[PDB]
Structures are given as C-alpha cells and as structure tokens.
Image (cartoon, grey):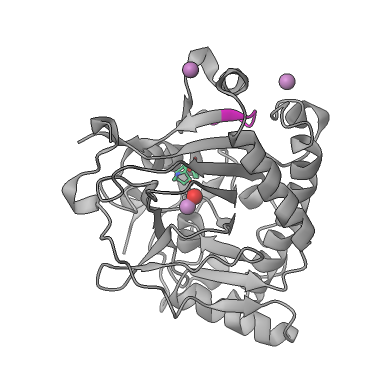
C-alpha cells in the first residue's frame, strides 16, 4: 500500500472486531408508541440503530445500489468529468450541491482508502438533477426517486424523535434538515487492511444520516474504547445520529462514532444520506428542553463556523463543538 494511505499506529483497526449483538434493530410496523419508545431508547443509549419494515421499497433500494455500483464501474475517462481541474474535490466549505468525486483524509497526514461521489438532493429541481452524473443513463431517474423516499423516511424518524423528546412534531422540518447530501462511497480491495482505513472514526457532523450497506466494513465505537462490527442487512437502513442532534438534545441523545475498515479481496459500495442544517443556521440546545436541572451544555454557534472545524480538525471526534462547550 502507498505511504499516502498508512494510518497512524493508534488509529489502525484490529483484524478481529466482534459483531455488535446489542445494535438495536427497530421494526417500524410495530404499534406507534412501541416504535417511539424503542427509537428513543436507541437514541439515548447507542446513537446507532437499524430500521426494518421502514416503508421504503426494497426494489428501489436494490435499483439504487445497482446504479451506484454501475457508476463506480464507469471508465476513468467518464469519471474525469466529476473531477474539478483534473482531481477529486475536497470536503471543505463551500461544499457545493453539484455532483463531484471527492478524496478524504486527516491532516501525520494520510488519505482514506475511499472514492466518494457526493451531491445535494433537496429540493429536487432541473438545475440540481442536471448537475448529477450523466452516466449511467438511469442514475438521475432512480436516485431522484430514492432521495425523495429516503427523505420521507428520515422525516418520519425525526418525528418519532420529537415525540420521544417532548418536542412539537415537525421541530426539524425546517432549516435544520434543508441540506440532503447523498454520499456514495466506493472501497476497492486493499492489499494491507491492517495499515489503512476506508473511513476514519467520526461523528456525522449533520443532524441525522441513513446508511444503506450490503457488505461488512462498518464499525461503531462503544464504551471503554471498544469497536464493534455493524451487521449488514441489505434491506435495512443504519440510522447514525449526528453531532448536531447531540447538541440540540443537550446530550440527552448520543451521536454515533463509526469508521469503515478495508477488505483485501472484494470491493464495497455504501449509500449515505446526510440530512442537516443549511450553513446559515444557528445551532443550540432546544430551549424547550432546558431548565435549572438541565442547563445548556453548548452556547449558540454558526453551522458554517462549526463545519470549517469539523472538516479540518480530526484531533478529537467532537473537535467541531469543543469551542462552544459551557457548564
Ligand atoms: C467521512 N466523512 C465525514 C465528514 C464529511 O462530511 C460531510 O462533508 C458532511 C456533508 O453534509 C458535513 C456535515 C457537517 C458539516 C459539514 C459537512 C464527509 C464524510 C462523511 O461521511 C462524514
Ligand atoms: O458519514
Ligand atoms: Sr484525474
Ligand atoms: Sr450538467
Ligand atoms: V458517517
């Protein structure tokens, strides 16, 4: 493996990470109150859960994974059209909603063993969809339907979260969910998995993420610096609560800290829908939940200012919010 991809010793993954048997799997076709209670418990104790019987068509999930795999099978010459000035774009502000291929890493500087296609999805209009990949031919029609369906499911989950917290329904149906970034992640086979990371350990900086996977590689950090493997369920969504939701709930909910490990023999594609605030938003603990017993743990901050730190400073998982901590 190229020196560029060698992770610092302490960040390298151990070869045998155990299955997370305690990852909540939540059936959304249970009675309404049972769903609210199970989602609430998962948000308080874990910050990562899977949803099944979630109402999003299994056929559409399969068609979306197919067209995403088809995109990454495209020739080099086609992929160049998504590389501004001949190279992948960087995860840095301004983060544009037009489709680009991205490189990612940490500044002991190293790169993640990953190619990412990213674009905005909300609101859908001709200008946005015309900025998506031209190939495969069916990408735009399949991913347009997928993005609307994933958003509908995410807003359902945010209203379950509202009921669990005692916030009015639709609390997040505003500026706090107006950006929908779809990240299609491609992990090619890696000759030295013991030295590399597909994705470094992170909170998602946004509000909430729905992740579609069909192969192993996703790992979560739980108490006592233990990593566990998240079982791939091809017809489920992994829900990762973001650092933004951790702040707004005043740490009543956990954020998901997770990473992706490489594989020596086979490639892997994942589809992450990252929903969260516009860069113009002010983030603070929900005042409705604050009291003398529950004082705010964060001062109000600019999401844009947070974003710059979150994307550049990887010294700690919550480096993005450290400047805004109080009490
Ligand atoms: C592994 N990387 C993490 C950081 C970066 O995330 C982003 O780029 C999101 C995209 O919404 C973002 C969130 C909050 C503020 C700025 C950007 C790209 C990817 C994501 O999978 C999460
Ligand atoms: O992510
Ligand atoms: Sr190039
Ligand atoms: Sr175009
Ligand atoms: V993530």
Front position in the image: 304 or 62: 62
| Residue 160 pos. (x, y %) | 67, 73
Front position in the image: 317 or 85: 85
Q: Which residue, as the protein is rendered here, is positioned at the far left?
A: 9
Front position in the image: 53 or 79: 79
Instruction: Please give the count of numbered marks on the rendered protein.
Output: 0
Residue 107 in view here: no
Q: Is residue 96 magenta?
A: yes
Residue 278 in view here: yes
Residue 282 vertical placement versus 118 (above, below): below
| Residue 313 pos. (x, y %) | 31, 40
Q: Quadrant of the C terminus?
A: bottom left
Front position in the image: 162 or 120: 120
Residue 72 vertical placement versus 31 (above, below): above
| Residue 128 pos. (x, y %) | 74, 30
Q: Quadrant of residue 307?
A: top left
Q: Residue at x 33, y 53 (%)?
A: 317
Q: Residue at x 79, y 36 (%)?
A: 138
What predominant SS class does the magenta segment belong to? loop
Q: Which segment is the magenta one?
A: 95-100
189 relative to 268 in the view: left or right: left
300 relative to 277 in the view: left or right: left
Residue 164 vertical placement versus 10 (above, below): below
Q: Quadrant of the N terminus?
A: top left
| Residue 146 pos. (x, y %) | 75, 50
């Amino acid at each position: 493996v190229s020196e560029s991809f060698v992770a610092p010793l302490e960040k390298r993954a151990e070869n045998d990470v155990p299955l997370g048997n305690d990852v909540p799997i939540i059936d959304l076709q249970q009675d309404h109150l049972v769903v609210v209670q199970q989602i609430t418990k998962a948000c308080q104790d874990f910050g990562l859960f899977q949803v099944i019987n979630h109402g999003l068509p299994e056929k559409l999930m399969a068609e979306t994974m197919d067209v995403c795999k088809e995109f990454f099978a495209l020739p080099a010459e086609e992929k160049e059209k998504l590389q501004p000035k001949g190279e992948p774009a960087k995860f840095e502000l301004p983060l544009e909603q037009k489709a680009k291929l991205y490189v990612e890493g940490e500044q002991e500087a190293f790169l993640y063993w990953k190619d990412t296609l990213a674009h905005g999805c909300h609101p859908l209009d001709e200008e946005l969809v015309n900025s998506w990949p031209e190939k495969p031919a069916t990408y735009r029609e399949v991913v347009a339907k997928y993005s609307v369906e994933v958003r509908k499911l995410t807003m359902r989950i945010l209203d379950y979260i509202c009921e669990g917290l005692g916030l009015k329904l639709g609390y997040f149906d505003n500026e706090l969910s107006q950006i929908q970034m779809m990240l299609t992640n491609y992990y090619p086979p890696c000759p030295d998995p013991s030295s590399t990371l597909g994705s470094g350990g992170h909170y998602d900086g946004n509000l909430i993420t729905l992740l579609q996977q069909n192969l192993p590689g996703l790992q979560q950090l739980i108490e006592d610096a233990k990593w566990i493997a998240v079982e791939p369920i091809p017809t489920a969504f992994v829900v990762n609560l973001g650092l933004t939701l951790k702040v707004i709930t005043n740490e009543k909910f956990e954020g998901s800290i997770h990473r992706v490990v490489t594989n020596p023999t086979r490639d892997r594609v994942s589809i992450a829908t990252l929903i969260g605030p516009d860069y113009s938003c002010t983030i603070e603990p929900a005042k409705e939940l604050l009291s003398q017993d529950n004082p705010p743990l964060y001062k109000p901050y600019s999401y844009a200012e947070f974003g710059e730190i979150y994307l550049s400073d990887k010294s700690d998982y919550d480096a993005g919010v450290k400047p805004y901590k109080i009490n």
